[PDB]
Image (tube, rainbow over the protein chains, first blue to last red):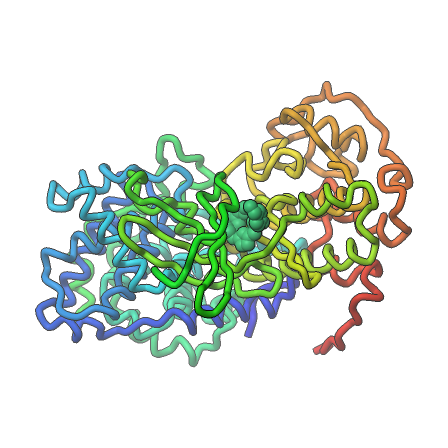
Length: 274
Length: 298
Ligand SMILES: COc1ccc(CC(=O)Nc2cc([C@H]3CC[C@@H](OC(=O)NC(C)C)C3)[nH]n2)cc1
């Protein structure tokens, strides 16, 4: 089903169909690391968690991080045999491509090389970004996990005007659901479920199946497998509580929720196992 | 990178360096945009990464096709479909005789189809001007140059300010709106529509304030009734002179009743009330070009 209201700029079922049909073009493999026998799933978590901290330092948007995450996972599905010393170059170059796509004034190249502690030069990043984009067939416009959460939050707070393009939702509850998704994305087994399913399952744990189905269009049976998989991650967030909305200098308060944050969730990921 | 021979330079501008190339074995002609990466300290330009990713998912008959992206030496080649002329040259060549009304209607209809396709794919063009509208010798017109384009989310957030060339920039951009979306492309197309009819730019301003006043002198100085929230916009000033809205019988004399109606809805001050590309296709101005498809009322 389609949760979007009647759209004045296009057919509501047409816009939603295109968004759904796009996910058929972008493929994800939850076991792409089997193509790289020398790598381990925990290495992917450490890299993504490091990219989260890099985004918060330069105040990059959450969309920028999840773009780099999707670029990283899809590029690895096309490659074979990667050493751990090459992971940092692929990760920071994915963030470099993502920053230039999403940010109005992205950081310069040398800043991306600066955060690598000299392990990645500027020319290495420029070489890596071309190999990433060419291997991905220049398919660099996916619907990230956080993009779906942005859609689900707008539909949850729709009025009689049905204006779905003007953002209107509480920022504090948004960053709480994104906090759960930031943990689940560290586990490589999340790729088994589509990005739209993961975002809807995280919203369900902070609300209900009725609100989930109203704003996502997916029935409870579609996300039950994802919800049951997300079960350990949700309680670890519930045991420690939810974070507060932060303020960033130079960033307007009406956009502060869109800035990527990072708290030490390393031990939070291992508590979800078993 | 072979089998292609440069025939003529098409142009050098914000897009890059465009050449006309022709395949020697097949006779196929293309447009090659050359990007010399040795001069780009930030790697592939952001406008290049944006345009490539957007066009590889915007396959439409009224959108200039990106055929291939070739990385040869320290350069990046973008292979485009070739069209022989842009709309601005065609309007200037037709300035004395005037573009025939059926051709104006056909061109606007195709432009609205390509624009409705972009907007349904959640993509804003943000630089619709006659120089970016290309025509072939078979009656087709296509949208080109997506370097300033951006995919918008649902809901949108604050995007880049001061977009669109000045003559075709919507009034909400000139007044410093925080959010914007598909309405800015419709305004540009409305300016292009009137320019085809009158063979002259509708609002040829030389500054941001002069552009806004030229719009005010034609459509009237807007107020809260015609545009709710206009007096609260950052660049709005209570000292704006009060001009009366001009009768479209003088703004676009050759335009009939259905034409003036469509143009009025494309030039509505309120972006929320401005007609959409999809709705414009259903306007009675195109009642002879297209027929309504049966709608499932389920
Ligand atoms: C010297 O002789 C000439 C021959 C033909 C022209 C018109 C033309 O531009 N044809 C194209 C262009 C194209 C592509 C090249 C990049 C894209 O366009 C732009 O981003 N910028 C354009 C609007 C300049 C589409 N495909 N076909 C002009 C002069």
